[PDB]
Structures are given as structure tokens and as C-alpha cells.
Length: 67
Length: 156
Length: 105
Ligand SMILES: [Ca+2]
Ligand SMILES: [Ca+2]
Ligand SMILES: [Ca+2]
Image 1 (tube, rainbow over the protein chains, first blue to last red):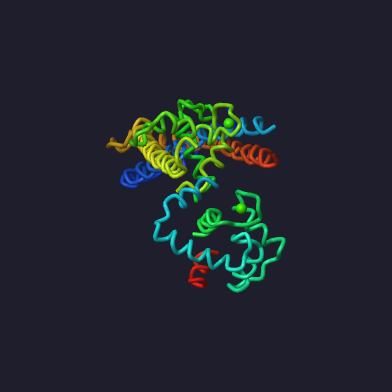
Image 2: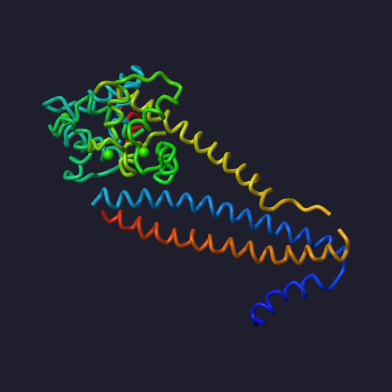
């Protein structure tokens, strides 16, 4: 019985629990491309993060070696 | 960026080292010591489209004055003529990692030595001796990020 | 010097010739590592019973709200790292010829 939970799990009812099956067949796809594009952004945001750990590890050496 | 200019001087066609040697004997028509000084450089700069300052005149000669005489002789003149005929610091950083295989932040010898053997060319023992100390300008045994830049300035 | 300064340049020019190759292929072991992990994570769809098909779109609808939240908390680490690099980088930062031959010959 949480206010933010009852409303969060209610965005499904208003978005799917209301109409057609051929709207559904052409909506569950659009609801899946949105995920592949969102797990691609997450992939590149991971490879970019690994790379920054190196730039900082190198920069952390330069600020010291040049002291 | 220096020892990149002696590589153009080393590979000048002798058909070019005639035109420059000729244009040098004219350059010095009037000099006592037979070499380009501030007087002869004043002439061919303003009589080419400038009017440089005599304190700035000596700053174009002292850049190739590997003799400290204030005069640009012939061998100092080709080094002047190759400075007037590279690679970005952002691009040399993504390449700096492919050297750093252990991903520490340096390039010890065994990481340079392996990049050299991958070039397909025939490598010697003396090549890796001069090269390692062309970058390791403090003899710590590795080429940190700043050194790897002054190392590869202008390397196409 | 133990070797000519034009071989020293020939060798320098040859190291960077494969470092871009060793990078153009590192960006290909990564182009695939994406698509491979983009079929383990986002396994392609395949079709259902008009009603018990709806309990899938609602699972996809909340899958997104979970994915884009996973994508945020990693973005705010990439974002906070970009802020630190410039904060790091600023610290360490603080520590003619052809016209002559024509007019002489
Ligand atoms: Ca001199
Ligand atoms: Ca290393
Ligand atoms: Ca060093």
C-alpha cells in the first residue's frame, strides 16, 4: 500500500490493459526495439566507463610523476 | 621534433641538394665567414615580403644554429629548408594504450620491443637501444604519457 | 647515434601503422561483443493468445522502466568520471622556403 508503488504499477494498466490485439501485435514490437536501443546505450556506456578508468589511472600517474 | 628534420635532410635527392647549395652560395654573396648571418637574412626576407626585427632575425637562425656561431652554414641551411616544406595529441592517446599491454600507465621495454617485432620489418639490437632512450628521457625505463608525445611529434 | 635518424623515423612511423590496426580491430572485437551480448540481453521476440499475450507487453513495459534505470546509474558514473578527468587534466596541465627558391634561381 504505497502511493508511488500503486501508481508506478499502474502505467501498465493505462498503456496496455485497454485495447486491440492487432494494436498489441504492433505495440509489443515497438516496446522491444525500445529495449534493444536501451541495452545498446547501456553497452556503450559500459565500454566507455572501462576506458575512463584507464584515462584516470594514467592521469593519476602523470599528476604524481610531474610533482 | 628535431630528429624528424634530419630525416628529410638525409633523404633529399642530390638533384635538390644542388638547387639548395646553389641558392646558398647566392645567399652568402657578401658574407665574410661565408655563411648566412643576420645581414644576409635581413635581405632575402624583406626583399621577399617582410621586414623582420633584428632581435627576431637571430631567432630564425638560432633555431638551426647547431654551432652557436649566429651563422647558418650549408648543413644548417637544409635543416632550415626542411622546417618549411603531424599527429594529434588526442589520437596518440588511443594509440598509447595499444603499447601499454599490461595497462599500467607506462611503456617498459618489453612492451616497446613487442610492438617493434610486429612491424614486419627486420629489427636489431641497436635499434631498440637508441629508440628506448629516445623516449625515456629520464632513464626510468618506461615512456610515460607526456614522454610518448614529445617522442612521436610529427610522426605521420 | 647507433642508427640513422631516418630509420628511427621509419620505425616510429611503423609502430603507429599497426597501433591503429590494433585499434581498428579492438573496435571490432567490441562491435561483436555488443551484438553477442545484445542477443543474450535482448533476445529477439517471437509470437500469442490475445489475452495471455497482454501479460507480456506489460512485462516489456516494465522491462524498459528497469532498463533505462540501469542505463541511468551507469551514465551518472560515466558523467561523474568526465567531471573528474577535466578536474585531473587541469591539474597536470598546470605542471618560408618555396617562396625563396623562386626569388633566388
Ligand atoms: Ca652555425
Ligand atoms: Ca606498461
Ligand atoms: Ca620515462
